[PDB]
Amino acid sequence: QQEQTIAEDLVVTKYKMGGDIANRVLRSLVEASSSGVSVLSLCEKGDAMIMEETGKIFKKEKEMKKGIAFPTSISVNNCVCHFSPLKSDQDYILKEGDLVKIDLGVHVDGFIANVAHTFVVDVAQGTQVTGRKADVIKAAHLCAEAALRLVKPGNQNTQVTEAWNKVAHSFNCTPIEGMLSHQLKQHVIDGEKTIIQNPTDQQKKDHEKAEFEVHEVYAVDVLVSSGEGKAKDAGQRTTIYKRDPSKQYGLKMKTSRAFFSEVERRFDAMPFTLRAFEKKARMGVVECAKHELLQPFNVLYEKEGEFVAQFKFTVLLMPNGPMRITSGPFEPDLYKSEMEVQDAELKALLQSSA
């Protein structure tokens, strides 16, 4: 009963302002991406820009929390998600032709605006991206377009799941199995109401069918692969975590207890990167993650040589229709695929207005 929702104009404003910041920071990072650029540097730049820009709004409200909802993550080629290296980790240096996914989130007073975008590094003027890179990027963006049209009051999450499989297969691509798009609420990045990608038979049973409703907010997250779509851990150090306020445990080590306290104060229940702490965080993390006080956002990979594309946007289900508050700077004429959507209903859906 105490929820602040988009029924309130002020709440819509807070979402829109966080969305404007997310959009601006994303575009800055895309422009800063060129051959030879350090992924660590881009992650640090993104996060700092989020803090600086949120610092400049609602200045008179000195107690209002605002800042990072999802730390800047830059996941290249077959890397799926959540790459945000520690200073001590192996960095990654961008190469011409790399496929890059930038994923980040901003919050204003707990209202979250998440965005992610895919592009290719240093595409030359007057050329197009072709091949499997083009296939997977076009597939992922058409999945995003389909979701923009289908995530509306009265529709079912299952409709989205089905459409995504049809679109992706049109390009001989596969949405990554089991990945979720969450409803957002104030202070809640991971609402239990979700859209699931390409669920296994077991995932279909464990996942709840649901109907979208007016005043709900979603961070729609499309991740599509040129390969089988069964993402796996590959020994990469997890750096992104979130506190889970539903779980409690009295920690045995003073370092763990103090780390717990610092996490709660600084981040509440927003995902954060360990780079925000490096040694003393590493030990505190161990006990907290072990007893489920922190949830990891692991770095997952598709098969070597394959490509994973992503588009994520946040949408407000307003009485007058869906209102998207974030998006990436997608240029369709850049991508040429041998394939196209052939399905009549799907083609109709994609040509219709959003």
Image: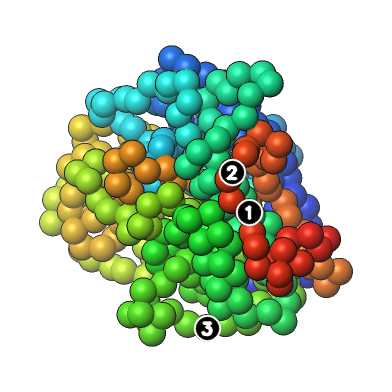
Q: How many marks?
A: 3
Query: What is the quadrant of the C terminus in the image?
Result: bottom right
Query: Residue at left 66%, top 18%?
Result: 125
Taking depth in this image into account, of 214 and 228 the one nearest to the observer is 228
Query: Residue at left 43%, top 15%?
Result: 36
In what element is the residue under mark 2?
loop
Tell me if label 1 and label 2 are in contact, CB under 8 Å.
yes
Amino acid type indicated by mark 2: Ser
Q: Is residue 183 above or below residue 223?
A: below
In what element is the residue under mark 1?
loop
Amino acid type indicated by mark 1: Glu
Please tell me the numbered disc located at residue 337.
2
Judging by the rendered image, the residue that carries numbered circle 3 is 209
In what element is the residue under mark 3?
loop
The span from disc 3 to disc 2 (Cα, nearest Å) is 34 Å
Q: Is residue 64 above or below residue 168?
A: above
Which one is earlier in the sequence, the residue at label 1 or at label 3? 3
- Regarding residue 152, the answer to whether it shows in the image is yes
Q: Is residue 336 above or below residue 194?
A: above
The answer to which image quadrant residue 291 occupies is bottom left
Q: Nearer the viewer, mark 3 or mark 2?
A: 2
Question: Which residue sits furthest front?
Answer: 338
Please tell me the numbered disc located at residue 340.
1
Which one is earlier in the sequence, the residue at label 3 or at label 2? 3
Query: Residue at left 55%, top 73%?
Result: 162
The answer to which image quadrant residue 32 occupies is top right
Taking depth in this image into account, of 84 and 121 the one nearest to the observer is 121
Tell me if label 3 and label 2 are in contact, CB under 8 Å.
no
